[PDB]
Amino acid sequence: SPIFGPEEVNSVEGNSVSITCYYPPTSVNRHTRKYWCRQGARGGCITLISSEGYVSSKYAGRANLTNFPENGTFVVNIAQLSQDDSGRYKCGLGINSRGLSFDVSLEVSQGPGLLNDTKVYTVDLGRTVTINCPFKTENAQKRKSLYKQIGLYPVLVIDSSGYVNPNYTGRIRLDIQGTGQLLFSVVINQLRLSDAGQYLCQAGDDSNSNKKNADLQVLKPEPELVYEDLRGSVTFHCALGPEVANVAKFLCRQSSGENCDVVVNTLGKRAPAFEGRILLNPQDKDGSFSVVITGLRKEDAGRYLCGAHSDGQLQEGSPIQAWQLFVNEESTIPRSPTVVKGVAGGSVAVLCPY
Amino acid sequence: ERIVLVDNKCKCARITSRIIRSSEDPNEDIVERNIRIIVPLNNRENISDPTSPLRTRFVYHLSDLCKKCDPTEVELDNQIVTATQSNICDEATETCYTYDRNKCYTAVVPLVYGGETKMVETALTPDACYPD
Amino acid sequence: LLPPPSEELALNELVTLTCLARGFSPKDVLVRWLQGSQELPREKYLTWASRQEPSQGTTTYAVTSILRVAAEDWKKGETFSCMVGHEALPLAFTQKTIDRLAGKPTHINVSVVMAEADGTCY
Amino acid sequence: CHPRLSLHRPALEDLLLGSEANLTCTLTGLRDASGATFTWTPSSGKSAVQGPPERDLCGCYSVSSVLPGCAQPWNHGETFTCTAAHPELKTPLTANITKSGNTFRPEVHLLPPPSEELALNELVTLTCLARGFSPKDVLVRWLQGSQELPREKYLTWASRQEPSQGTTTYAVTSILRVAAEDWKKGETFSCMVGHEALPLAFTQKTIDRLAGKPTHINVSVVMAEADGTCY
Amino acid sequence: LLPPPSEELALNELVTLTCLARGFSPKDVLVRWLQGSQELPREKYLTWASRQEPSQGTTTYAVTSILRVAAEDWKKGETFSCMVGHEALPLAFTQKTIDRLAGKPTHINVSVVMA
Amino acid sequence: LLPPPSEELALNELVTLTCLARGFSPKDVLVRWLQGSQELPREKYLTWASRQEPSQGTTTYAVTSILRVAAEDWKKGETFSCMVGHEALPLAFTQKTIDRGKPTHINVSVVM
Ligand SMILES: *[C@@H]1O[C@H](CO)[C@@H](O[C@@H]2O[C@H](CO)[C@@H](O[C@@H]3O[C@H](CO)[C@@H](O)[C@H](O)[C@@H]3O)[C@H](O)[C@H]2NC(C)=O)[C@H](O)[C@H]1NC(C)=O
Ligand SMILES: *[C@@H]1O[C@H](CO)[C@@H](O[C@@H]2O[C@H](CO)[C@@H](O)[C@H](O)[C@H]2NC(C)=O)[C@H](O)[C@H]1NC(C)=O
Ligand SMILES: *[C@@H]1O[C@H](CO)[C@@H](O)[C@H](O)[C@H]1NC(C)=O
Ligand SMILES: *[C@@H]1O[C@H](CO)[C@@H](O)[C@H](O)[C@H]1NC(C)=O
C-alpha cells in the first residue's frame, strides 16, 4: 500500500526497460528483502530476481536489481525482451504472502519485419508534421489527391486546390517550391488523436493508379511519477516549448469520465478547495513556469495535465504534459494546528516544523 | 470493509465496519462489522527463547482492543483543555502474541572466550535491529 | 454515552442522545456537548440536577443530560461527544465520543487465518 | 625456492567476542635468515614484534610480524599496507588489505531429528545449517536450555562455496548428539551463528519436542464480545 | 534425508534438501543425488568432507550434502533421492526418497469459542 | 511397492507386501528385501520369473514377489523396503520403502 511505481509499461522485442519502485525510507524498509515476481495464475507468485543474490534461470545474463536507500527507490533492468514476457508482475518488500507490493503491467509488441516500404513520421500530440510527396515531370494537370482508407474506401478529403473536408478545416496549406523538381509539401498544424492511420499520397496521376504511402504515428505523453506524503508539498514543472509563450496555460486534474477540472488558469481562475495553498509563478525566457501546491490531503492523488489554449481549458488539439501523484500517508511529518484564533489587540504564536 | 476502527499489532487483530445501504427495504440498512485474526503457530508464550512451549491458547477481549487511553485536546470556550478518553486504563504489562515489524527484540547469552565469560547480545528479528 | 433508541430512527425527524455520569462523591459536576469539534451553545440541550443514589454502603451521586439532533446527519456520519468535568479526575476532564459506525452491528464476519509462515504481523 | 609475501585479515572470534585485533604480515620462501624490517602506514603504537622463525618445506626461513590494536580502523573501512625489504631478493615486495564490501547475511535453519531415530530411544541428532553469506568467516555455538555447551561435544565442518545462482555465496553445517530422555522431558536446544554482516553480530534459533515433526496441532481461539459498541 | 524448513517456502525462490550419513568406520564414501530416475550432474550440488565425530566408544565418521531445487517443481509433486556408497554395505548402496507430503502433520484440531 | 488390502488387516494375523517391476528391456533382474537397515535371508519370500507384457509396439517385461510379515511390529511401525537390480540403471540399483499413505484428519468446532 505505501509502494508505488509505473502502472503500465510498453516496449518491443530486443529492447531494454527500466522500472522504478518507491517505498517509505524507514530503517526497516531499507534493510529488508526486495523482490520482483511474476504473478501468474495457479496460486503462486514466483520470484524472478531478488535483493539477496537470487537470480533465476530464465533471467541469467539479462537482469539485475539495485537498491538505493537514500532515495527510497529500487530499480530493475531487463534486457533482450521477448513476447513471452507479457503479463502481470509485482514489486515488493519482505515476504510475498503479505501485501507490501504494487502491481505492474507489461506488454511487449512484435516489431517490424519485411514490410519497410514506407517512410514513417512520429510526432507529439498537438504539434506540426510534414508529409513529403515527390511530384514528377508529367503529372501536374490532374488531381493531387490524398486518401485515407477508412475501411477500404479511398476517402479523398484533401485536395491541393481547396477541396477540403469540414473536418480538417483551418490548418492545412501548401507552399510552392516545385515547378519541375521533385518536391512539394503540406504542413499539418495542431494534430489530434483522431488523425492517425495510413495515408496513400499522390501528386497528379498517370493512369495505373500508382500508389505512395506515408504513414504517421501520434503519441500521447508519458506521465512522470511524483512521490509525496501527507501534510507535505509538491511542485510541477511545465516545460512546453517557446512556440506557445504568448498563449494562456493551465493545469487540470483527470477524473473518471474523461473530465479535466481546472485547478488554475492564467486568466485568473481557481478552485475553492485550493484557496490559501497554491502558487503560480511568472514564466521565464523559455516560457517555462512552476505550480506549487502545499498541504497535501489524501484525495489529491491522481493524474494531472498542463497545457495551453486561448481560453484556459482542456481542448483537443492542444499540447500537453502529464504527471502521476501518490500521497504516501505513512508520513513522518509532525501534525500541527491548522487554525489559530485570536482577539483584537492580543497576540498569537505558531509553531513551524522543519 | 470500509472504515478502520482497530488496527492492533501486539495481538495482530483488525476490525473494520461499513454501512451497507442494502437494496430491498430502501429506507433501512444494516451495519456490518469485520474482524480478522491471524494466529501464529510457532511463537512462544513470553518472547524469550526457553520460556515455556509454543502458545496453544489465544484470547481476545474486544473491550480491550477498542480501548483509548492517550490524552486528547479539546477546545471548549476559547481555551485548550486536556481530557482523557476512557473509564478503564488503570495500568508494558500486556502480553503480545506476534512481533511487530518496526521494533527490535533482543536477548542476552553468556559465551566463553578462553578465560572469563561475556554478556553477548543477540538479535531475534534481524531486519529491524540495525543502528540507523 | 448511549445511542438513540431503535424506534426513533423510523420517523426520520429527530433523534435523542443520553449522557449518564455516576458515582462521584462531591455534588458538583460540569456537562458540555460538542459536534465534530465545535461546542454547541448551552440553549440546545437540557441538563438535570445532581442527586444521591440508593446506598451501596457509601454516599455517591448521579446526573443526566440529553440532546436532540437531526435524524439525517446522524446517518450521514457526524460524531458527537459528551464531556464531563469533576474535581476528582486526574486530568480534570474526560470525554466519550459516539457515532453511528461505532455501534451495535447487525452482521458480524469473523475470519481466522492460521500462519505457519511467520509471526511478525506486517 | 623463491620467496613470497602475503597479508592476513584478523580472526573473526577476536573481533566479535574480544577486544584486541592483530593483523599479520608474513614472509616465506626466505633462504637462510635476514635482519629485515617492515612498514605500516598507520603507526601510532606500531610495536611490530617479530618473534622466532619457523622451518618450512625442505628447509626454508619463514618469519612474520604482527600489528596490534587495529579493530576500529578495520571496522570503519580503512586501509593497511605492508612492505618489506631483505637480503635475498632484488626489490621490496608489497601487499594491501581492506574490509570487504557488498556482503550478505546468513539464513540460519535448525532441523528436528529424523523420525526413525526416535524409536530406538538411545540418542538423537540435531542439524544447524547456515546459507547464503558472502565472506567465508563464520562461528557456530550450541546451548542447552540457557547454558553454553563445551566445544568438544559437537562437530562443525568448513565453509565452502555453493553452486551459483548469481552472486557467489557460502554455506556451513554442524550436528549435536543429545540423550533421548532430555528430548522427551521437554528441554530446549539453541544454535548460534555469528557473522560480519549481521546487525548485532549474532543471531539464534531454538527448537524442542513440540516444535518440529509435531504430529499434533492444538489451537483454541476465544473471542469474548463481538457485539459490543466499539468505541 | 530431512525435509525443508518452513521459513523457506514463503519466498518462492528455491527449497533446500539435506542428506546426512553418520557412524561409519572407514572414512571413504560417495554421495549422489537423483530426480525421479535421472542422475544429476556433479556441478548441481555441494558435499562436504568426511570428518571424525566426537564419541568415546570407537572411531566413526560423518558427512553432509545439500541440494537446492526449484519451488515450482516442489509444488508439482516430484521426488528426489540421496544415494550413499560404502564398503561395509552388503549391497554397496542405499537410497532415501522425499516429496512434498509426509512432513505434513497427522491431524489438526481447531476450536473457536464465540463467548 | 503396494501397501497392505484392509480385508486381511482386519483379521490381524499377517499381511502381504507386493513389489512390482515393469518396463525393462532385457529379461534379467535381482530382487532382494530388507527391513530397517538389515537384509533378510532369501528363504523368507518367493519371487516369480520374468514374463513378457504385450503393449504398444516394443517388448518389455515384468516381475513380482510377495513378502509376509508379522502384524505386531507393522502395527508398531517397523519399516520395510524392496530393492531391484538391473544394468540399465546408472548406479545399478533402486529401492522403495513403505511404512504404516493416510491423509490428514481435520476437526473444526465452533462453540456459541
Ligand atoms: C519475559 O522474558 C524477559 C526476558 O527474559 C523477562 O525480562 C527479564 O527478566 C529478568 C529477571 O527478572 C531481568 O534480569 C535482571 O537483570 C538485572 C540487571 O539488569 C538484575 O539486577 C536482576 O537481578 C535480574 O538478573 C531482565 O533485566 C529482564 N529484561 C530483559 C532481558 O530485557 C521478562 O520478565 C519476562 N516476562 C514475563 C511476563 O514472563
Ligand atoms: C536517486 O535516483 C536518481 C534518479 O533520478 C539517481 O540518479 C542516477 O544515478 C545513476 C547511478 O546509478 C547515474 O548513473 C545517473 O547519472 C543518475 N542520474 C540520472 C538522471 O539518471 C540517483 O543515483 C539516486 N540516488 C542515489 C543516492 O544514488
Ligand atoms: C546491471 O546494472 C547496471 C547499473 O550499473 C546497468 O547499467 C546494466 O545494464 C545492468 N546489466 C544488465 C541489465 O544486464
Ligand atoms: C592493492 O593491491 C593491488 C594489487 O593486488 C593493486 O592493484 C591495488 O591498486 C592496491 N590498492 C591500494 C589502495 O593500494
Image (spheres, coloured by chain):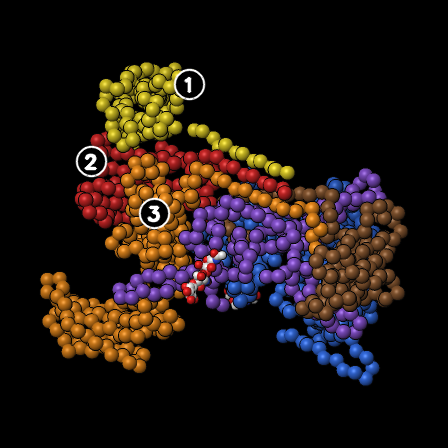
Chain colours: A blue, B purple, C brown, D orange, E red, F yellow
Q: Which residue is mark 2?
A: E88
Res. E91 visible in picture: yes
Q: Which residue is mark 3?
A: D127
Outermost residue toward the bottom? Answer: A345
Q: Which residue is mark 1?
A: F10
Where is the C terminus of chain A found, in terms of image quarters?
Answer: bottom right
Q: Position of residue E25 (x, y in %)?
A: 19, 42
Q: Position of residue E17 (x, y in %)?
A: 38, 43
Q: Which mark is residue D34?
A: none
Horizontal side of residue C73 vs B103, given as left or right: right
How far apart marks 1 and 2 lie (CA) works out to: 40 Å
How far apart marks 3 and 1 lie (CA) works out to: 40 Å
Looking at numbered disc 3 in the image, what kind of residue is underneath it?
A: Thr
Q: Is residue C64 above or below residue D227?
A: below
Q: Please tell me in which quadrant of the rendered image residue D2 appears.
A: bottom left
Please state the quadrant of the image where ligand 1 appears.
Answer: bottom left
